[PDB]
Image (tube, rainbow, N blue to C red):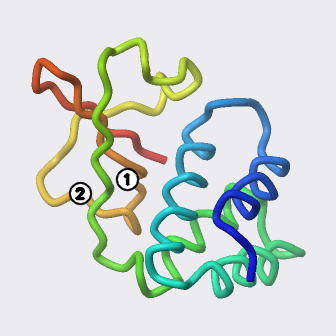
């Protein structure tokens, strides 16, 4: 079996840019998949509807819609020290967090500052 880190780097390589929301989503998919022994499934859903099939971003989103661990799953909260600790490329994807945010509905994660303020990352 493939490690979360390795599968992540494989995914990163298909992604335009750096530190985008889709990067953050890769990190979320690989973490949550690892917690569930689903990295196999995920790796294959990424390749199956990769070619062709969908764009890499679309293979990612399709993973959050098709792979069972993500259905009705709340986005993970990531605690950060400052508003600066959010990758610049994520800035144009940040939104206020609504009630009951869902990963399969596009919410990558929720950034929780020290002041208590939250910023949601949406794809």
Residue 113's place in the image compared with 51, above or below, is above
Is 45 displayed left or right of 31 in the figure?
A: right
Say whether marks 2 and 1 touch (CB < 8 Å): yes
Question: Would you say 112 lies left or right of 121 here?
Answer: left
Q: CA distance from mark 2 to mark 1?
A: 6 Å
Q: Residue at x 31, y 33 (%)?
A: 95
Q: Quadrant of the N terminus?
A: bottom right
Residue 10's x, y, as percent?
81, 58
Rendering quarter of residue 6: bottom right
Q: Residues within 10 Å of mark 1 (few under 14, many from 20)?
A: many
Residue on which the image places disc 2: 101
* Position of 91 relative to 14 (above/below): above
Residue 57 lies, in percent from the top left, at: 68, 55
Res. 26 mark = none
The residue tagged 1 is 107
Q: Where, by quadrant of the figure, is residue 113 drawn? A: top left
């Amino acid at each position: 079996d493939i490690s979360a880190a390795d599968l992540a780097n494989i995914m990163y390589d298909h992604l335009p840019g750096f530190g985008t929301a889709f990067h953050q989503l890769v990190q979320v998919i690989c973490a949550l998949g690892a917690d569930s022994n689903s990295l196999d499934i995920i790796h294959a859903e990424f390749q199956a509807s990769l070619a062709e099939g969908d764009s890499p971003q679309c293979a990612l989103i399709q993973i959050t819609k098709r792979v069972p661990i993500f259905q009705d799953a709340a986005p993970p909260v990531i605690h950060i020290r400052s508003r600066g600790d959010i990758p610049r490329a994520c800035q144009k994807s940040l939104r206020p967090v609504p009630p009951s945010p869902k990963i399969d509905r596009g919410w990558v994660c929720v950034f929780q500052l020290q002041d208590g303020k939250t910023l949601g990352l949406k794809i």
